[PDB]
Amino acid sequence: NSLVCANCEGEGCVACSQCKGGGVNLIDHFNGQFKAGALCWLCRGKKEVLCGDCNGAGFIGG
Ligand SMILES: [Zn+2]
Ligand SMILES: [Zn+2]
Ligand SMILES: [Zn+2]
C-alpha cells in the first residue's frame, strides 16, 4: 500500500535544493562553470524541482 512521502510530505514538487528556492546559483561551483548569481543550473529559475524520493508522486508504495 501507499504512504505519503516523508521527504516532501505529499507536495510532490519541493524547493530547489541547489538555489534553495531563490532561483540563482548560491556559489561558484567546483566544476568551474556554474557561477554564483547566475540562473540556477538545476531549476533554471523556477525555484522548485520534483522530489527525489517519490519522483513527484507524493506517495511511496509498499
Ligand atoms: Zn516526495
Ligand atoms: Zn511545490
Ligand atoms: Zn534552483
Image (cartoon, rainbow, N blue to C red):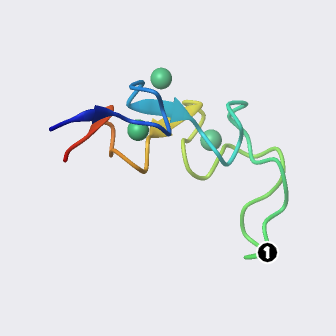
- x and y percentages locating residue 53 in the rendered image: 40, 49
Residue matched to label 1? 30
Q: Residue placed at 43% from the left, 50% from the top?
A: 52
Q: Residue placed at 84% from the left, 55% from the top?
A: 27
Left or right of 30 on screen, residue 50: left
Left or right of 8 on screen, residue 61: left
- Tell me which corner region of the image, top left, top right, bottom left or bottom right, holds residue 40: top right
Is residue 24 or residue 49 the one in the foreground? 49
Identify whether 12 is placed above or below 27: above
Q: Residue placed at 78% from the left, 74% from the top?
A: 32
- x and y percentages locating residue 50 in the rendered image: 41, 40
Is residue 42 or residue 5 the one in the foreground? 5
Please tell me whether mark 1 sits on a helix, a strand or a loop.
loop
Q: Residues within 10 Å of mark 1 (few under 14, many from 20)?
A: few
Is residue 19 or residue 8 the one in the foreground? 8
Identify whether 18 is placed above or below 24: below
Q: Residue placed at 71% from the left, 37% from the top?
A: 20
Is residue 60 or residue 36 the one in the foreground? 60
Callout 1: CB less than 8 Å from ligand 3 = no
For the N terminus, the image quarter is top left
Outermost bottom residue: 31
- Tell me which corner region of the image, top left, top right, bottom left or bottom right, holds residue 4: top left
Left or right of 24 on screen, residue 59: left
Q: How many marks?
A: 1
- x and y percentages locating residue 24 in the rendered image: 73, 40
Amino acid under disc 1: Phe
